[PDB]
Image (spheres, grey):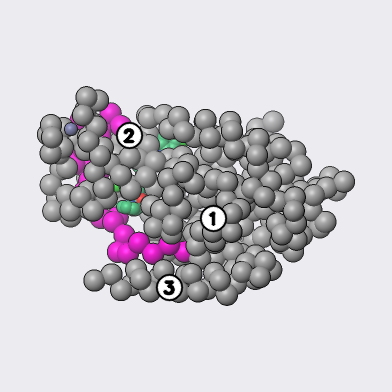
């Protein structure tokens, strides 16, 4: 009746190595980068919204909003200095996605994260839909210029506490983040339209599937497509209040599996089942060593 022979990680692994599973879409959120030292600035425990008094804001969310930013970019860039990572070292989860790419299984990774770790882990622009944008590149805001600047340039400006201005036209330069008040990139909708005709497996890692329209991606899968959640908490189920949600646990469940724990440990377990654990270990050890050894 169903593509998975059982609703377990082992069933998913068996399906993945069957001839029926050729194209995997990953949907990822902040949970895949916390072990890298990047806080989930949507979890209250990080306390982002609490410390934001030194920036003297009209309301807390204005520092994440596009119009305020264009009028007053200094608070955003001071906060960006405060929150700048000490290192950019992707996680076992990120490299698991790189292994998917290497094995010819990765159709697309849709990410909510702006932290660039997918790119550092070796996913290419074509592999990625950065649904909420990214720090990886920045652009002059003037429509007639749009000069692109890499993260190293932006970092130099942020740490020297100089507001980044375009070298060609002296306009403000903004990281390619989707600020509040901007629309998600057109790439998100056009890729969605094409990719979900083609997907054999949805791997949902490190996201509670609460932010829209990203969360709605799980309902774009074909009805037969298995969907594996690797996350500290079960998520994406139909909300009993607000009227294609995940069904892990009912008598009617047939394709959705929940593996509850840290994303790294779930990806290690899945890799072990697939026979990839040594490959993943070697890839992570050498990439981490190269990052640690940046001189
Ligand atoms: O996610 C953030 N900062 C970490 C980071 C990641 C990659 C590159 C630079 N910074 C971040 C979130 C909200 C507001 C600001 Cl201002 C920064
Ligand atoms: O989450 C979003 N953007 C990321 C972000 C990070 C730091 C500062 C501002 N925005 C976002 C924006 C607009 C609509 C939606 Cl649905 C999400
Ligand atoms: Zn410019």
Residue beneath label 1, please?
A: 101
- Work out which residue is located at the far top of the displayed protein and give it: 144
Instruction: Specify start and end residues of the magenta stretch as a single range.
Output: 66-91
As helix, strand or loop, the secondary structure at mark 2 comes to loop
Residue beneath label 2, please?
A: 65
- Crowd tier of the residue under label 2, counting other residues whose Cα lies within 10 Å: few below 14, some 14–19, many 20 or above: some
Residue beneath label 3, please?
A: 286
Q: Answer yes or no: disc 2 within 8 Å of ligand 2.
A: yes
Q: Is residue 87 magenta?
A: yes
Asked if residue 241 is positioned above or below residue 49 in the image, the reply reads above
Q: In the visual, does 177 lie left or right of 238?
A: left
Which quarter holds ligand 3? top left
Q: In the visual, does 146 lie left or right of 103?
A: left
**Sequence-first tag of 1 and 2:** 2
**Sequence-first tag of 1 and 3:** 1
**Sequence-first tag of 2 and 3:** 2
Identity of the residue drawn at 16% across and 32% down: 171
- Crowd tier of the residue under label 1, counting other residues whose Cα lies within 10 Å: few below 14, some 14–19, many 20 or above: some
Identity of the residue drawn at 53% across and 38% down: 214
User: Where is residue 21 drawn, in percent x and y?
Assistant: 71, 51
Q: Circles 1 and 3: CB distance less than 8 Å? A: no
User: Where is residue 104 drawn, in percent x and y?
Assistant: 59, 54
Asked if residue 58 is positioned above or below residue 23 in the image, the reply reads above
Say which of marks 2 and 3 sits in front: 3
For the residues labelled 2 and 3, the Cα–Cα distance comes to 39 Å
Identity of the residue drawn at 41% across and 68% down: 287
Q: In the visual, does 255 lie left or right of 176?
A: right
């Amino acid at each position: 009746e169903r593509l998975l022979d059982e609703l377990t990680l082992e069933g998913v692994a068996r399906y993945m190595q069957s001839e029926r599973c050729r194209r995997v879409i990953c949907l990822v959120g902040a949970g895949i980068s916390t072990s890298a030292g990047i806080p989930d600035f949507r979890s209250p425990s990080t306390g982002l919204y609490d410390n934001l008094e030194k920036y003297h804001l009209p309301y807390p969310e204005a520092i994440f909003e596009i119009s305020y930013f264009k009028k007053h970019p200094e608070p955003f860039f001071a906060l960006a200095k405060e929150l700048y990572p000490g290192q950019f070292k992707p996680t076992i989860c990120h490299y698991f996605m790189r292994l998917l790419k290497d094995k010819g299984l990765l159709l697309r990774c849709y990410t909510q994260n702006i932290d660039t770790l997918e790119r550092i882990a070796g996913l290419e622009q074509e592999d990625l839909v950065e649904a909420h944008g990214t720090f990886y590149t920045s652009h002059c805001v003037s429509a007639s210029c749009r000069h692109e600047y890499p993260l190293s340039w932006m970092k130099e400006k942020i740490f020297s506490e100089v507001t980044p201005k375009c070298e060609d036209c002296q306009s403000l330069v903004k990281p390619d983040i989707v600020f509040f008040g901007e629309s998600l990139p057109a790439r998100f909708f056009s890729c969605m339209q094409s990719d979900f005709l083609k997907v054999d497996l949805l791997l949902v890692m490190g996201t509670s599937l609460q932010v829209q329209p990203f969360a709605s991606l799980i309902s774009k899968a074909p009805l037969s497509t298995p969907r594996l959640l690797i996350n500290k908490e079960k998520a994406g189920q139909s909300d009993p209040f607000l009227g294609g949600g995940m069904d892990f646990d009912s008598k009617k469940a047939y394709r959705d599996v929940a593996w509850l724990g840290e994303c790294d440990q779930g990806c290690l377990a899945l890799a072990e089942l697939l026979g990839w654990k040594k490959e993943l270990e070697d890839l992570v050890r050498r990439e981490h060593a190269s990052i640690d050894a940046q001189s």
